[PDB]
Length: 114
Image 1 (cartoon, rainbow, N blue to C red):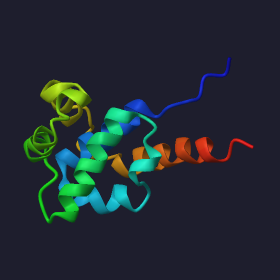
Image 2: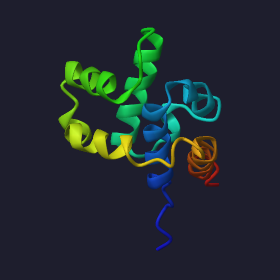
Image 3: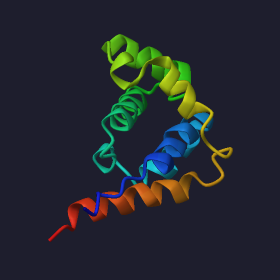
C-alpha cells in the first residue's frame, strides 16, 4: 500500500504553537481550517480553538482544556496529557506557519485524489 501521508507531527506543532502563541491563530487560520486535519483528536482541538476564538476567548492550553472539559470531550482527545504533550511539542512557534502549510498540503493531497 501507499498509506495516505498524514502531517501528525506538524499538526501537533501547529496546535502546540497556538497554545504557545495565541496571536498565531491568524497565521495558522490563514492557511488552514478544521477540515484540513484528518486527525480527529487534532480536529477536535482545532474546532475548540475555533469555537473559543469565535467566543472571543483565549486558545491557550488550560483555556482549551477546560473548553473540551465543558464538552466532555477532553478524554475524547486523550485527556489533559495529550493536550500537555502538544503544548510542549513545538519549537517556540518559530515554524508554525510552515507546519500549517504542510497540514494544508496533506489536506490538498486528500482532496485532489482523482
